[PDB]
Amino acid sequence: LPGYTGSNVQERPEDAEKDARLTLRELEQLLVRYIVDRYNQSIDARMGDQTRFERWEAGLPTVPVPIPERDLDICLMKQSRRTV
DNA sequence: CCGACGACAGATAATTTGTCACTGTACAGTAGAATATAGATGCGCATCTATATAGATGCAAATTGAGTGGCCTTATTAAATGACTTCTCAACCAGTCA
Image (cartoon, rainbow, N blue to C red):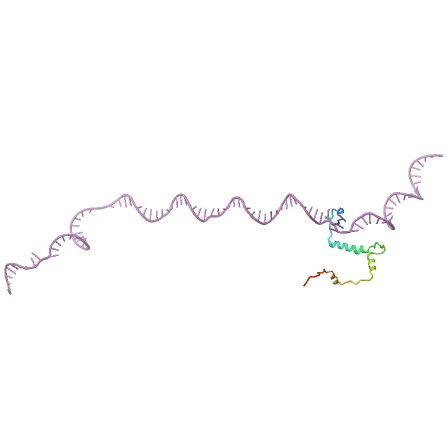
């Protein structure tokens, strides 16, 4: 991708600050595709004969029930001891 | 007759491509950021300038009131009016008469 910075400062492409082009919305639209079409569909290397997704789906002990989006309110931060 | 070179055919490792097994290495919070400089621009405060004088003064007409200088017939009489001055202002005795 354009604007690539290398794995460290000694390998930084000198054009990285001038050659940047993508916004966060482009990078996510590339990265999500890469994870859904390529990466989860590639071979689990320990096995050699299953995809990562195929091994996940077949590896569930049972199909879990989807949790309600409201019940993810367990994500809300707690203030423990404020007084009325 | 003997030796050298070309045509055609045949066999072959070098080259390239593909497949397969073993492996060094990055994933591990991290370079946008700090520190000088020149150069232009803008707001504020001071430091002059040039204009604008009205009040005071000097002077020169313009009367203005107040001076001063120069030029002029006279003698008798009479009347009138108004004045001034002077003078004067006794009292009983002696001689007639109806």
